[PDB]
Length: 120
Length: 120
Image 1 (cartoon, one colour):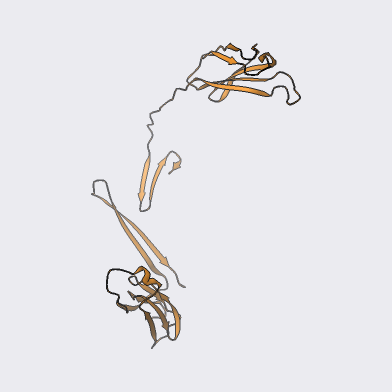
Image 2 (image 1 turned 90 degrees about the horizontal axis):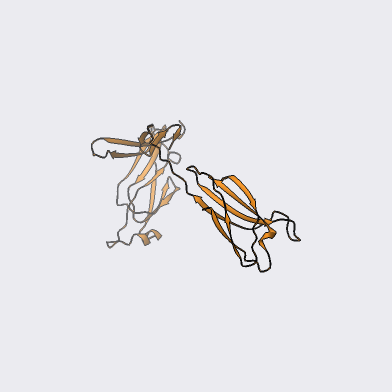
């Protein structure tokens, strides 16, 4: 969950040329962003350690991305060349006992069901 | 004379297989199915006292192509005919349905009443 293996598949490019970033998303919204650099020659595999926070019953998702450190003839600083995402933790589902009532009215052509301020 | 403060209808219960209708020389229309009724409103083309009803009946029609039952081919006004009068404002159609509870004990009645106005 905290350990990730990066593999450089460029023929003639070191991964040091790119700005690394990782983000953690709680139920879709983010909560933690960090930048990093990683040295890896063409072909090489390198490990990446990501400290994780204590996590409540929400659903957590990591996203790891590389971008352009500075402008290029074909694109501007920050442009994203590669990303991958992973489920950290699934969510805990709640189930709630409902005590409140529901009415019902039958007529020739309709069944009517009332609950709070909604009629079906 | 007391019929003309009301709406008058000419009802054929059955005719096989096609027929035209004239009233007092004039052409009211036609009808094709041999086993359901034909009804005409005649309040406008009818006069107090003596009135002439003329009916032309054909044995074979395009309606015969759907009446190829394993049975004798007959023809002619083979069910009752009659006139009757309703108030200007009258009950055109009724649909009565009935439900029964899960135990088949208690009942519900579902009533549709269609009304029709003609100058009331």
